[PDB]
Amino acid sequence: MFKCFTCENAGDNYNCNRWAEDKWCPQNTQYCLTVHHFTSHGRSTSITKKCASRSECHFVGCHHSRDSEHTECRSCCEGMICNVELPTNHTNAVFA
Image 1: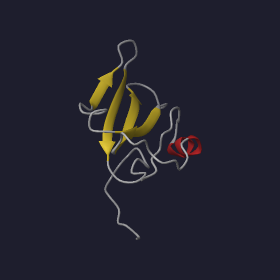
Image 2 (image 1 turned 180 degrees about the horizontal axis):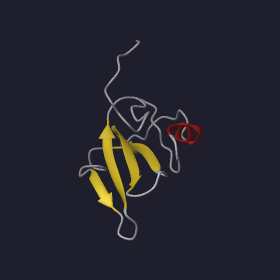
Image 3 (image 1 turned 120 degrees about the horizontal axis):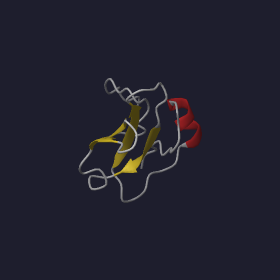
Image 4 (image 1 turned 180 degrees about the vertical axis):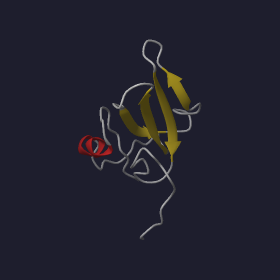
């Protein structure tokens, strides 16, 4: 089992943590979805993540809003609570 960030409305990474606690992921899941809401014009940016699978996000990518000019890029990262910070640089080591 593993713990992932299953937050909904979180303006910042910290907030996402306050909502999404350290709970085990579902049985029908093997990935950590990570949706990034980037506004074409505006500092504010929505963020949402949760457990997913190969089917749930079989066709990842970005989706530009029809009404607003805000795009939503969702991906699938592996590893316990891998969806820590939005701006992913690289993978760290294990302390096991």
